[PDB]
Amino acid sequence: SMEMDEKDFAADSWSLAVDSSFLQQHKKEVMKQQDVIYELIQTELHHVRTLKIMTRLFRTGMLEELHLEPGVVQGLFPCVDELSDIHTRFLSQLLERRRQALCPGSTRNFVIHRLGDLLISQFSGPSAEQMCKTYSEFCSRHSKALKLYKELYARDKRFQQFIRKVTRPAVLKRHGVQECILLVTQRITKYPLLISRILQHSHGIEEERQDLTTALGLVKELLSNVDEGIYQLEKGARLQEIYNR
Amino acid sequence: AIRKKLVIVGDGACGKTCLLIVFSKDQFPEVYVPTVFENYVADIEVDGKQVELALWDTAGQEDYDRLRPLSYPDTDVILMCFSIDSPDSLENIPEKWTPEVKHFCPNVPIILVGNKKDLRNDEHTRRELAKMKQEPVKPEEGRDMANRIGAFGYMECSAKTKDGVREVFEMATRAALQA
Ligand SMILES: COc1ccc2[nH]ccc2n1
Ligand SMILES: COc1ccc2[nH]ccc2n1
Ligand SMILES: COc1ccc2[nH]ccc2n1
């Protein structure tokens, strides 16, 4: 993550991020809506950061420092570039919506009144097809990635030293290889929870309540399709084991 | 410090997310209670042993039978949650959550946890449940269910007041350590 965005999302809530003289100008219902929208953007910034640790710290470090067999790094980090592209673009749109809403003379005081339209755009058309295809591939390769990691850590000394070295800093405490993989798999199922709570506090404008209701429906359709398209791949699986499912 | 993995399971309104938030947070959430929990690695010292306990939530995965099991690999301890204000969350334990956890986490200790124990003496809770011919889950009903499902143990807590929260995670650490 970059310092500007980390500082903008350092507070535990929107009510603590904005100036107290700005907070006092809003109704409690607007504050509750903004606290949940702030949590969605903050968790998206963290999710994009998890993908950057996977691509830049782990993947690139293994390619430039280790002598692994070809196709081993891809097996540990399936679809990470496609996932980074999807979420970095989504994050850019959320952060631009926040930026446009800032008051002149402020870098922290804003109210986002129109999130629904951005969520419908993200969870419909080509971007939804790309998310569905990429998560169906990633989640089907999840178990294989974890097993490959465990095999490499148990049998390769240089791999163990590499992992222990790059995961040593306290800021990486929650972000080991297996932890990153599960954080990415669990991300998609956080969206309906966040969207439903934003919707609970967005009844003031009927257009907004409708847009968030449509967005919630699209996210659920996307999740149902991903869930139906998953079948765990296993290294060395035989065709007979596959067609006897 | 040895690394252990904990996963919490249970119905959507069982309070599992709130329990993980209250345990992990430095300072109780007085201004905003988060909607979701990402992960956390708690430094715990129980009975003289230091453990790094990775904490994971299954919230949002309840309707997705192929995504949800991806949370289980290499779990060392399961917290199986129900809400004391919801006798229906306790009924879903033996033939929905228990067979799933036994299948994906064989030989992993399960601690059955009754959440929201503060609502057992809440008059609004008692009036609402009485309309559907119900009452808050009794301590003996929780213990009997834990006994029936082969749980390692039975515990109660309140995320709202923090009572019993530290004890649940210290016991989970002890269960994860047993060979
Ligand atoms: C029940 O009290 C509160 C306080 C702050 C909040 N922010 C969003 C929901 C919400 N609820
Ligand atoms: C913490 O309160 C929450 C959590 C998740 C939610 N989804 C919809 C409302 C809602 N509230
Ligand atoms: C959620 O998927 C599964 C798969 C196999 C199972 N056996 C018992 C419960 C169960 N659930």
Image (tube, coloured by chain):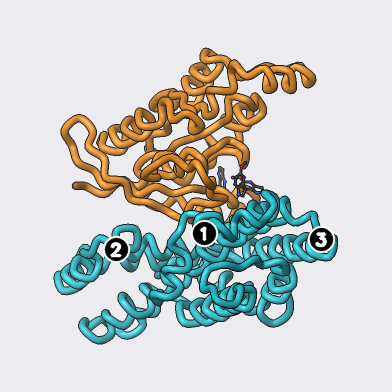
Rendered cyan, the chain in question is A
Nearest the eye: B115 or B92: B115
Q: Residue at x 39, y 27 (%)?
A: B152
Q: Colour of chain B?
A: orange
Q: Residues within 10 Å of mark 3 (few under 14, many from 20)?
A: few
Q: Name the amino acid type tagged 1.
A: Gln
Q: Nearer the viewer, mark 3 or mark 2?
A: 3
Q: Residues within 10 Å of mark 2 (few under 14, many from 20)?
A: few
Q: Which mark is residue B39?
A: none
Which residue in the protein does label 2 denote?
Answer: A171
Q: Secondary structure at mark 3?
A: loop
Q: Residues within 10 Å of mark 1 (few under 14, many from 20)?
A: many
Q: Please say if the residues under marks 3 and 2 sit with CB atoms less than 8 Å apart.
A: no
Q: Secondary structure at mark 1?
A: helix
Residue A108 screen position, x and y as percent: 52, 68
On screen, residue B116 versus residue B78, left or right, reads right
Q: Name the amino acid type tagged 3.
A: Ile
Q: Secondary structure at mark 2?
A: helix
Which residue in the protein does label 3 denote?
Answer: A205
Using the numbered discs, state the Cα–Cα distance from disc 1 to disc 3 in whole angstroms. Answer: 31 Å
On screen, residue B103 versus residue B129, left or right, reads left
Using the numbered discs, state the Cα–Cα distance from disc 3 to disc 2 in whole angstroms. Answer: 41 Å
Q: Residue at x 75, y 56 (%)?
A: A202
Q: Residue at x 70, y 60 (%)?
A: A220
Which residue in the protein does label 1 denote?
Answer: A186
Q: Earlier in the sequence, mark 1 or mark 3?
A: 1
